[PDB]
Amino acid sequence: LEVLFQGPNEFETLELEHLLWVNITQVKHSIERAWTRELKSLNLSTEKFAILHELMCLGGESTPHTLARRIVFEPHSVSAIVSRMEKDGLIIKTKDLKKHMVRIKLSEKAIDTFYQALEISNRVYKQMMASITREEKVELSKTLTKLRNHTLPLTHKHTKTLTPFKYI
Amino acid sequence: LEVLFQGPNEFETLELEHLLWVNITQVKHSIERAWTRELKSLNLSTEKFAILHELMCLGGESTPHTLARRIVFEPHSVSAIVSRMEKDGLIIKTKDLKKHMVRIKLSEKAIDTFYQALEISNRVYKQMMASITREEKVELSKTLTKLRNHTLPLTHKHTKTLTPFKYI
Image (tube, rainbow over all chains, first blue to last red; front, side, top):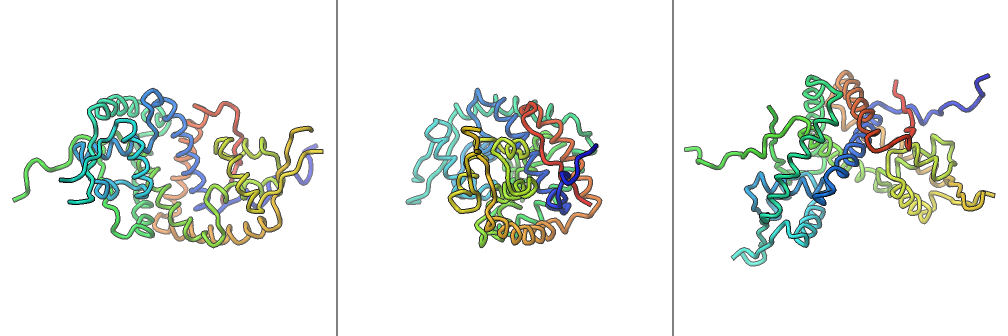
């Protein structure tokens, strides 16, 4: 009755650490796809939202090198997103009055867009994560933080001072 | 002595579910940056490795629609990566002998590249995750799986039957 020789092969049994990478990538993709669709009326990707948010923590104005130090993304990636945000009227770039340094500032449109986006985004993440308990959330953040702290210095050698976000 | 009015602002305190998204994105980025550098002599991104791995679970040969059902990525993304892998001699596309259906098969070069990549990749993930205990790993996979199972159906409605990877 069950067919022979068609069950899973050895490549479907993983080391646990490889399965954890697959789990992390699948949760990142599934949450981002759903969040991005909810935020589409504001035209925000997760990375544009992350840059608006970092610049709000910096008081709406900073420099490319300070923004890059605070955020996990590669500098070329942060510059590309900032340039797109500038075309969209979210960031204003001005020459420092230091030759060649640029200051980046959020426009009032960007700050009002962030007001709206933060409120929707908090509702989205809350409803997405409602099926795990407070205890499971607190443990997940602790374990992910241990992984971040052990793995970030394998390639980021004093280049990042990531924003020390808190929760209550 | 401490300066006034320069401490963090309200945007540095997040809802826990938003902080969990930041934690997931930071761990994904930090692990991928380190892994990609170790695998660079095989010219494999994490997504090319994931497609080679899914096709090994399928016995080295499948169709674009079956591959897409098994993997989390968007179909356009899977097609773009498969097309790049075809240019690189990793995938062979042949017309089905069904008009317009394509069969995709790993080349023997791709299977030998996967032999090498899987062994390096298992060592990389093991050393990256050595700072969390077996118990913390098992709980992390359980909690991430609950998040995946609750969030994937918000946008994938019977479109995916993700490979049921196991560990021991």
